[PDB]
Image (cartoon, rainbow, N blue to C red):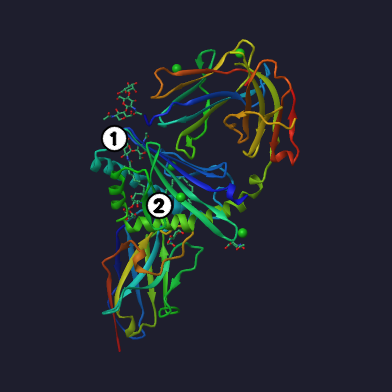
């Protein structure tokens, strides 16, 4: 219901940054979690999405093999491990949640996520 | 009135045979609204151990329920189903006729 | 037989007044009750070993959470609407929702809502839509409901995605139990009833529900009155096909047609 992102800052090119997200509500494990980003000018797009343990998470082709999504149901927190950062990755990173029933695939669009944090700012140089 | 009286039907799982275990069934149906009181009676006294199905409804939205209890009918025992509902003025008693 | 096994998710919500309310629910796969949802419980009980279908424990828990949220909000919404419109209590709402799978992986879904046993609105494609008879106060209620984009998305998700996938798994999980045939026991009796007798043709302990019982004069049907197919606590059924006749007519038979008899009928003469 309430999400707070943390871990944003300034990173040099080739750098690594670990974003985190805190959820306030109950049954965190049943919510679909997602990392979204908005760069100046460009629209708010998806970086990574995650749902059930057995299920493989989803990624944007630009961040495939570089970023990794994970959850810690016990610690009620969502993580984004950003590796080999580029200045292209400079954006406001948002944390999103939604109840998505079993017959439906993890949503790729931002319009489908219901809970949004105020976001974190990440900037990459060189 | 949008309200509808319940149709009470008393019957048994197997054709009655005195001194052998059978099941007494009471199917209450076609009533609106769902608030209803149903009891199975032995010799006019309420049977406590009765069981029932989860209240459900038909396509036409009218409700139905099945009350039931295991029992051994005896030649001198009189079984009935007592049902109360807003549409009724007195808890209606329908008797179990061995021939149904 | 796929059409004979639609999933019906039924909700009964009784609001005696501004304080008292209870919401109970069931699930039917064809004639079989697969689930139960009491107001006193946080979860939706499974009544069959195969009731989860092919859904994972965590897939099922997401649905449990959706339902719990749906329940509490549904009560909230109705209490608010009756206040906005001055619909005085007692109020009873009912929901028939689910789907039916067709061959070639196609499906059909529905969401029907009744108020005081009368249809008032339904979910159609992407939005709520009122029934043809429906009073004018319902058109205002739908306008507020159609503003809620998130809800319209979830019900499209449940009806279009979750439901077809659920029942396909229920049909594979419960394949064995769904294919059972329990042969009926049939007998004739003197049904008590001016100048008229009641002929009673008992058909009992049959499964599944489709049955055709008729009083005949051989090769000549009458004005047969097969009553309700009444239920038994073991999921078998009971039927009294009765005929209101004048004294004598004593050359009539009873023809009992049921799937468990494999093409042959039980004929009872009297
Ligand atoms: C239905 C298809 C089922 C598919 C397969 C099911 C598998 C499991 C089957 C076994 C159990 C069967 C038991 C029977 C269950 C009863 C029937 C099923 C009910 C379907 C639930 C639909 C859930 C969608 C609505 C919902 O999620 N909750 C809430 C909360 O939404 C709130 O929070 C949301 C996020 O948490 C959003 O922020 C939203 O904007 C905000 O408003 C919902 O979105 C809103 O309260 C709206 C109310 C609910 C819709 C009712 C529509 C009918 C009302 C008729 C009008 C009454 C007029 C009376 C005078
Ligand atoms: C709203 O509707 C509910 C449901 O009909 C009303 O609750 C019912 O209230 C009566 C009177 O308080 C209860 O009956 C009697 O209560 C006394 C104790 O006060 C007890 O000694 C008697 O044996 C008898 O039970 C009745 O149990 C209760 N029903 C339930 C299921 O709780 C409620 O009063 C209505 N409120 C308004 C604003 O009219
Ligand atoms: C049906 O369930 C609701 C929800 O659990 C019950 O409402 C609660 O009533 C108690 C008092 O009896 C309060 O403490 C709660 O705050 C109420 N709401 C919630 C959301 O907890 C309702 O009483 C139940 N109805 C019946 C007939 O038992
Ligand atoms: C129907 O869908 C299921 C699962 O997607 C598949 O295994 C099956 O072969 C499909 N059958 C047909 C006739 O399309
Ligand atoms: C769900 O099915 C209906 C009816 O076929 C259709 O109009 C609607 O657009 C579908 N919803 C989604 C999200 O595909
Ligand atoms: Cl008593
Ligand atoms: Cl519980
Ligand atoms: Cl098929
Ligand atoms: Cl329809
Ligand atoms: Cl008589």
> Residue drawn 60% across and 51% down?
C2
Depth order, front residue of A40/C158: C158
Q: Is residue C197 left or right of residue A77?
A: right
> Residue drawn 42% across and 32% down?
B34
Q: Is residue B51 left or right of residue A75?
A: right
Q: Nearer the viewer, mark 2 or mark 1?
A: 2
Direction bottom: furthest residue: A126
**Under 8 Å from ligand 1: the CB of mark 2?**
yes
Residue on which disc 1 sits: C19
On what subunit does the disc labeled 2 rest? C
Residue on which disc 2 sits: C123
| x, y percent for residue C26 | 48, 41
Find numbered disc 2 in the image and state the secondary structure of the residue it sits on. Answer: strand
| x, y percent for residue C46 | 52, 44
The C terminus of chain C - image quarter:
top right
**Under 8 Å from ligand 2: the CB of mark 1?**
yes
| x, y percent for residue A78 | 37, 65
Query: Does residue A73 sit above or below A87 in this rendering?
Result: above
Residue B23 — which label? Answer: none
Query: Does residue C117 sit above or below A42 in this rendering?
Result: above
The quarter of the picture where residue C155 lies is bottom left
The quarter of the picture where residue A46 lies is bottom left
The quarter of the picture where residue C91 lies is top left
Query: Does residue C197 sit above or below C62 in this rendering?
Result: above
> Residue drawn 46% across and 18% down?
B92
Depth order, front residue of C115/A94: C115
Marks 2/1: CA–CA distance: 28 Å
- Determine crowd level at label 2: few under 14, some 14-19, many 20+ residues with C-alpha closer than 10 A: some
Q: Is residue B86 left or right of residue C252?
A: left
């Amino acid at each position: 219901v309430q999400l707070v992102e943390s871990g944003g800052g300034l990173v040099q090119a080739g750098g690594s940054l670990r974003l985190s997200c805190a959820a306030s509500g109950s049954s965190f494990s049943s919510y679909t979690m997602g990392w979204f980003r908005q760069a100046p000018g460009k629209e708010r797009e998806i970086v990574a999405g995650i749902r059930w343990s057995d299920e493989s998470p989803i990624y944007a082709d630009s961040v495939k093999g570089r970023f990794t999504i994970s959850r810690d149901n016990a610690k009620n927190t969502l993580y984004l491990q950003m590796n080999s950062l580029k200045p292209e990755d400079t954006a406001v990173y948002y944390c999103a949640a939604r109840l998505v029933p079993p017959g439906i695939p993890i949503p790729r669009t931002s319009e489908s996520m219901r809970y949004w944090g105020k976001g974190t700012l990440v900037t990459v140089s060189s | 009135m949008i309200q509808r009286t319940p149709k009470i039907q008393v019957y048994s799982r197997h054709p009655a045979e005195n001194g052998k275990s059978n099941f007494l069934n009471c199917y209450v149906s076609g009533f609106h609204p769902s608030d209803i009181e149903v009891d199975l009676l032995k010799n006019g006294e309420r049977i406590e151990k009765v069981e029932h199905s989860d209240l459900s409804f038909s396509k036409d939205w009218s409700f139905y329920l099945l009350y039931y209890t295991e029992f051994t009918p005896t030649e001198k025992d009189e079984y009935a189903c007592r049902v109360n509902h807003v549409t009724l003025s007195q808890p209606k008693i329908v008797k179990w006729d061995r021939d149904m | 037989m796929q059409r004979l096994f639609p999933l019906r998710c039924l909700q009964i919500s009784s609001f005696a007044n501004s304080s008292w309310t209870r919401t109970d629910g069931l699930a039917w796969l064809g004639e079989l009750q697969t689930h139960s949802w009491s107001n006193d419980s946080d979860t939706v009980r499974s009544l069959k070993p195969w009731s989860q279908g092919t859904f994972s424990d965590q897939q099922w828990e997401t649905l449990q959470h959706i339902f719990r949220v749906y329940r509490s909000s549904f009560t909230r919404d109705v209490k608010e609407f009756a206040k906005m419109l001055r619909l005085s209590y007692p109020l009873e709402l009912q929901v028939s929702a689910g789907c039916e799978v067709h061959p070639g992986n196609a499906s059909n879904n529905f969401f029907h809502v009744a108020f005081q046993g009368k249809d008032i609105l339904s979910f159609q494609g992407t939005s709520w839509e009122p029934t043809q008879e429906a009073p004018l106060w319902v058109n205002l209620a739908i306008q507020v409901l159609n503003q809620d984009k998130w809800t319209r998305e979830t019900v499209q998700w449940l009806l279009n995605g979750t439901c077809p996938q659920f029942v396909s798994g229920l049909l594979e999980s419960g394949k064995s139990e769904l294919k059972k045939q329990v042969k009926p026991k049939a007998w004739l009796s003197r049904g008590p009833s001016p100048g008229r007798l009641l002929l009673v043709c008992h058909v009992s302990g049959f499964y599944p529900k489709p049955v055709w019982v008729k009083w005949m004069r051989e090769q000549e049907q009458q004005g047969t009155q097969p009553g309700d197919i009444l239920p038994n606590a073991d999921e078998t059924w009971y039927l009294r096909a009765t005929l209101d006749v004048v004294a004598g007519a004593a050359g009539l038979s009873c023809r009992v047609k049921h799937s468990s008899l494999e093409g042959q009928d039980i004929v009872l003469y009297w």
